[PDB]
Length: 178
Ligand SMILES: */C(=C/C(=O)OCC)[C@H](C[C@@H]1CCNC1=O)NC(=O)[C@H](Cc1ccccc1)NC(=O)CCC1CC1
Image 1 (cartoon, rainbow, N blue to C red):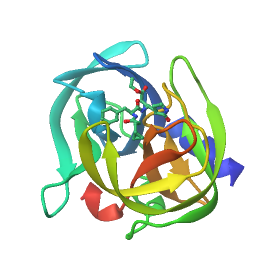
Image 2 (tube, rainbow, N blue to C red):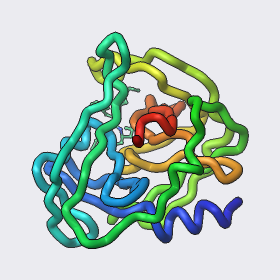
Image 3 (cartoon, protein in one colour):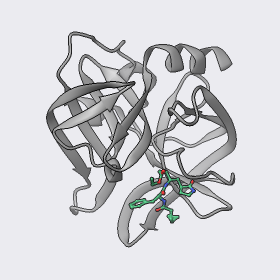
């Protein structure tokens, strides 16, 4: 399991920078990666020390038009991500003993035992209403956004916020990546 996180870290999780700061990016498949929406990847992005062009970005919102705090971006490169869509479940899932995989330039290859991840649903993220969020009782900190919540060979969510005592992720579901 530990192992999974390592295969992930090694082939799919990358250190990035936007005009907003340092983030962890998850490469899902082909040239498709997912980032927090507040990372504001414009027309370009920095992927580990090199400027990469973004061909298309999509800010995910739910049926009612409510923010989901996720942005899908298509990169302009000759590299392809290993397909990990099969590790993402079809339904937003809870989990026990999750692990938050962070890979930032300030926090590289960092594993954090966030513990149990439970349904939370609505959340007020700094003035932006947000849906489909999950919560863990761990004091997550700045510079950790974009981290990949994982558990038993599953990629379940993307860290997006925290209040000093708890952390919140945007749930991941396979239908998002088609
Ligand atoms: C991750 C990204 C980051 O580095 O922040 C901006 C550069 C952080 C991690 C959070 C912050 C402190 N502890 C954490 O675990 N996330 C945020 O800063 C994020 C800010 C934000 C701004 C705009 C839209 C969405 C999110 N945190 C929050 O919003 C937390 C505040 C309440 C609990 C939601």
